[PDB]
Amino acid sequence: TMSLGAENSVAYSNNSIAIPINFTISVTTEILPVSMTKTSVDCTMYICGD
Amino acid sequence: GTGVLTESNKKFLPFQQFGRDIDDTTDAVRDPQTLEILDITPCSFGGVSV
Ligand SMILES: *[C@@H]1O[C@H](CO)[C@@H](O[C@@H]2O[C@H](CO)[C@@H](O)[C@H](O)[C@H]2NC(C)=O)[C@H](O)[C@H]1NC(C)=O
Image (cartoon, rainbow over all chains, first blue to last red; front, top):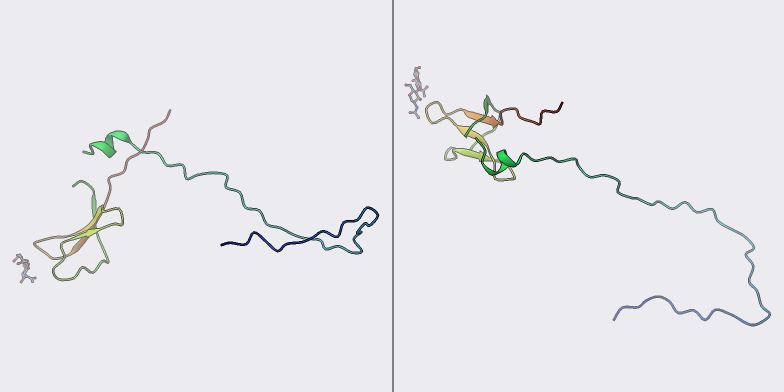
């Protein structure tokens, strides 16, 4: 049976805040399709042909 | 068939008579009189646009 992720009790209380001391600049790659091959088919030559 | 017949570098085995593309399409032949292998390429076609 699959595990959805590590469990984490967030350390919440009504007067505690966590502030980041430091950072990392992250570069992430996203790929997106934009076009197909522009195929076109002659219906008479496909069906019959000569 | 109908096509532009041309000389070719293909080496059929001694019993083989036709050659086929991935898409079944016959793309070479052996002449039964002088046992050379000919490529078949289709006669030129395409849309005409004004
Ligand atoms: C079919 O006949 C031809 C003609 O005899 C054979 O081709 C060669 O023809 C030349 C003359 O132009 C002869 O000098 C050769 O001896 C012939 N034979 C060869 C092997 O070159 C052809 O080989 C014959 N094909 C078959 C499958 O029998």
